[PDB]
Image (tube, coloured by chain):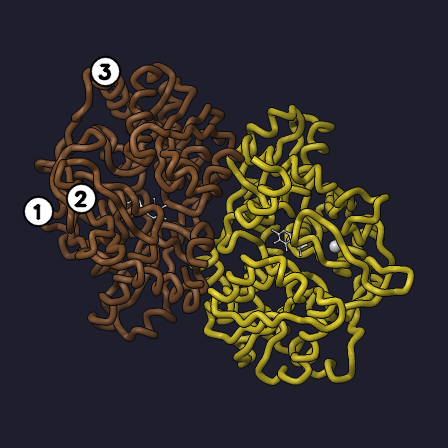
Chain colours: A brown, B yellow
């Protein structure tokens, strides 16, 4: 439950029962034969795991620095890493005898991931979404609806994510009997930060085995973008003990850190409690959840997972920020150079790995976690016009 | 070069040289050690091959018929099987010392797959596209530009695909020195129909091995949509000699065959000569390429590859049609039932297999080639269906 002084279970009495049932279920099942047999079956024949580790030769050479490898999570069914975590908890909820999935979503990306899983396993799916976001993400709402999920707008409060989260919790408290609260990142009250990370670690395991086959050695630096921090942890974890492996997390710099328009919790947030956990969040002078801005929809969460705040404390991992302008430039660069259109989120890690690579030696290895494809960001990019 | 009486090189004198050079180049590199090592390298680390073979348990049961398997070409990089051919030809062009890639495109899907492969191999890419189609595929045109490809609108003639094809041949005649003409389907003058199919057959091979591992036996019926016919030929080929395997190609029925508003060259076209080949095409009473209609963008090609006309003839394969309405229904079905949003093209194959399944025993296997994903079709479906 604790990663140093970050984490916990800051939740009402009402939520203690479900959370213990969940943590219990996860314990037994965590390594149960079948559950894993089933999970690996869907992950394989449905999600298309494992994803390849691609060496961006053209890009590296154009920079004349370290070797830049892309862990292709953009190729998993759905286009994003979120699918890993979604199949996991959905399958777990199935094993728990649950028949309904609920979740909140800012950009709508996690909502889609949940809807996909729900649909796959024949479970009812209700997605809470701040009316503000719903009117901003017409396509993801449409996408979730095509998959058979129900989108429940939230007009209470500021009609945003925090409001969706509250509504989601509300629903779970009363329906947890047959309803599972599918959290989308390594956040929320225990055991969520741990469960999500375990479900994403598979990224790191493959990426490890793959880099050993392609280079016969572990990488020098691993770079991933950080919103809640799930794709970062998923690929970070397997290398936490390999001391020589540097870990770099990239947060959204937005219009610039000094402009207040960003979503860099770790670099500009303060410690506090939100979503049932103790970690870094972006508040206002009154302890209220403050805005988030990033050309990247998925880097909207007003905070970051506890394990990341921890890793930052013990200095096992370094956390930087990249601006919208930089990410947007990286987006165009990969597309033109490697014929790969990355998600705007991923473009943040790419942007930084690029700077980093330039200041390194030809045979130093950098593994960038390409968390997703950018088909979904074409409209917003079409900014460039 | 000939599949029965279909195929050939019905082209101008100026094109016989580049074509012979290409065929020569393909002959040697076809099985060269290096070439293939690089091809398999890119197909794996960049395109993510192999794609899995998924069992739509929920769908099969909901129909209570044969087992419905899905060859997931929707998971390949780019979201469509077109990438397999784009890589293969781009790579071949590289080995030939070409530095430029040209291509025509109707919906812009082949345009996108060529742009990606060009970007991957540092080649210059110019895409010819009828102005008509350019103005109707805003997102793909943008996609191609993002990939660093130059989109050349064509306003001559009817401003459509046939006009785009004429400009592409034109260009190739003058620039074949350093420019490779990358055809997107099993169509065109020899050796194209053969090269494209070879680059797509990897789909069938994988699917063959994968079904044997999942069912220990070959499938009863293989179903794939058919535009030009490349994803159908890619998954069919490996099973041609397996006489017990049923082969069904599905064409665009559009508004309904009798309406004439479709794109079913095999089921309603006539033998003809176009794009340098003798095969089935949709032509008006004046031997002119007729407009096609389909809710699925990629089934717009006004004809079909010669090898499919041949397979139809000798009856090795059966070809049916599915309407926009039916494909659209499968689109929604697959999405809610398996959590897989198929391409409208593939929705045609899915729609038919579904019908075919219901009239089969539960021990019978059907393999549908899910040629692509539906992210690219959300806009049209939003308008057409609503919600
Ligand atoms: C949601 C998303 C993110 C950010 O979330 P994390 O939990 O921090 O990984 C990053 N990349 C993509 C492609 C996403 O969809
Ligand atoms: C272009 C396309 C087709 C049709 O072309 P074929 O050459 O007949 O395969 C089918 N499915 C998808 C997903 C396509 O993009
Ligand atoms: Na056709």
Q: Is mark 3 within 8 Å of ligand 1?
A: no
Q: Is residue B352 visible?
A: no
Dot in front, 1 or 3: 3
Of the two numbered discs 1 and 3 on the same chain, state the one appearing first in sequence. 3
In the rendered image, residue B377, in percent from the top left (x then y), is placed at 58, 47
Residue at mark 2: A308
Residue at mark 3: A14
Q: CA distance from mark 2 to mark 3?
A: 28 Å
Vertical side of B137 occupied by B19: above or below: below
Q: Is residue B204 visible?
A: yes
In the rendered image, residue B267, in percent from the top left (x then y), is placed at 83, 49
Which quadrant of the frame does ligand 3 lie within? bottom right
Residue at mark 1: A314
Locate residue B94 relative to residue B259 in the image: left or right: left
Tag of residue A139: none
Of the two numbered discs 2 and 3 on the same chain, state the one appearing first in sequence. 3
- Density class for disc 1 (Cα within 10 Å; few <14, some 14-19, many ≥20) is few
The residue that appears at 86% across and 44% down in the rendered structure is B258
- Density class for disc 3 (Cα within 10 Å; few <14, some 14-19, many ≥20) is few
The subunit carrying tag 2 is A
Vertical side of B263 occupied by A28: above or below: above
Q: CA distance from mark 1 to mark 3?
A: 34 Å
Along the line of sight, the residue nearer the viewer: A296 or B205: A296
The subunit carrying tag 3 is A
């Amino acid at each position: 439950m604790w990663f140093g002084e970050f984490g916990g279970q800051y939740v009402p009495e009402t939520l203690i029962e479900p959370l213990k049932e969940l943590e219990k279920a996860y314990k037994r099942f965590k390594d149960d034969e079948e559950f894993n047999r089933q999970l690996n079956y869907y992950l394989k024949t449905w999600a298309g795991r494992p994803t390849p580790l691609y060496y961006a030769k053209r890009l590296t050479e154009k920079i004349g620095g370290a070797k830049i490898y892309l862990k292709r999570e953009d190729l998993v069914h759905g286009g994003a890493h979120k699918t890993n975590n979604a199949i996991g908890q959905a399958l777990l909820a199935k094993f728990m005898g649950k028949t309904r999935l609920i979740a909140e979503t800012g950009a709508g990306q996690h909502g889609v991931a949940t809807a996909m899983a729900g649909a796959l396993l024949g479970m009812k799916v209700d997605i809470y979404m701040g009316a503000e976001d719903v009117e901003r993400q017409k396509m993801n709402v449409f996408r979730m609806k095509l998959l058979g999920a129900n989108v429940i707008p939230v007009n209470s409060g500021s009609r945003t994510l925090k409001d969706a989260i509250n509504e989601a919790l509300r629903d779970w408290v009363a329906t947890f009997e047959y309803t599972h609260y599918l959290i989308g990142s390594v956040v929320g009250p225990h055991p969520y930060p741990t469960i999500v990370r375990d479900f994403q670690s598979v990224i790191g395991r493959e990426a490890k085995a793959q880099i050993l086959e392609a280079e016969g050695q572990l990488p020098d630096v691993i770079v991933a973008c950080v919103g809640g921090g799930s794709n970062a942890m998923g690929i970070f974890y397997p290398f936490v003990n390999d001391k020589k492996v540097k870990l770099v997390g990239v947060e959204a710099g937005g219009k610039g850190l000094e402009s207040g328009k960003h979503s860099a919790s770790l670099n500009a947030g303060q410690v506090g409690v939100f979503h049932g956990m103790l970690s870094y969040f972006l508040q206002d002078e009154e302890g209220q959840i403050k805005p988030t801005h990033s050309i990247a929809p998925g880097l909207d969460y007003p905070g970051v997972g506890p394990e990341h705040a921890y890793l930052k404390k013990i200095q096992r991992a370094e956390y930087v920020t990249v601006t919208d302008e930089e990410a947007l430039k990286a987006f165009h660069e990969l597309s033109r150079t490697e014929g790969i259109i990355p998600a705007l989120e991923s473009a943040h890690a790419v942007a930084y790995a690029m700077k980093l690579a330039k200041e390194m030696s030809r045979d130093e290895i950098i593994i960038v976690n390409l968390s997703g494809r950018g088909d979904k960001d074409l409209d917003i990019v079409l900014v460039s016009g």
